Image: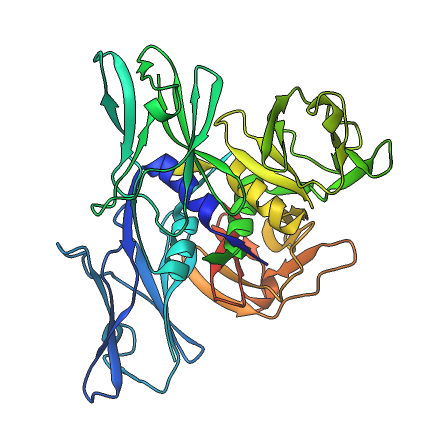
Length: 113
Length: 113
Length: 113
Length: 113
């Protein structure tokens, strides 16, 4: 089942006081325009050196080094680094996982269909 | 025991995409200056009509109507409304709970000692 | 909004390994039978000295000392202790909150209507 | 940072009422005895068709079909299925992730070193 997130947010607030994130995926199109080639998150967490896994149509493309968190707080995942130098035809399913370096845990942060 | 909040934040991020809060307590002093008379949170949640309970030195002063969330995102709790028109000597312990209107749950968001 | 509890359960599992609870409310009827006089939880947490608040029809009856966690893992809340020695007519709304002694937080664990 | 799990457990309790799990890893040794060949969890979740990924010394061995949840509530991960038919020398690091089929999320449930 599911549960309301109110108690979790206030528990988080009491512990960390201040938190701002924005994982709204901004998908970048490549060449040709029907190719998805990047995804950008406007405000990522910065407390650890997070890395990202990409899965295309059920195929695990693995993990690559992260581009930097930029001064505007954003972080870009370049799918060319994962897909042998190519973007991804936008008919495919794309899933992007962030990886917690303390555990190896994978959490979905972007999905395209 | 305790647990790392990483998995909870990313689970929250996936669901709500964007969240910014700041419950760093800004304590206001009154008359005399050794009296605590308000507490202000710079960026509160706005998804529900949250209310606040105040407890002073183990005595539950109860719940009062909320002042508004202001255009800068802040919300003020005026202890005069709870303590029969008086501020609170700063030697006391003060605890402020936010109340989830869907459940009646109380969550600590500010403590003075 | 809400979120799936899967990630929270597995995060909990990794940290505590083993957990069993059962807060299915067992409501006891008193004299007359149309009075609710107790509520029992079959398997409560035992890591802290939890206490309970009772609210009847919007009136906060406050907190009382806990009866013991029994050898079968159960814990009983006797509404007579909270309501001046009387049970509660079953037309009323009843809400039972458990209180975390580390924070003062109140969490709903039983509601009657 | 970290946070106390009290609020999460009681939020879970209110929603699901009853929950029992036990992910204490029981490691099985193979042939020779210095090989780790299985890991068993005494009481797994059963609400979804969870699958497991195994990582040995930083190498992702991938995902395989799950053995069944047995009538005693247990579930076994046979490392022979993941490691080309072989157990794992117990000097290696082994990490077992459970995978949420709704999201693809990976959560650590067992680690050997």
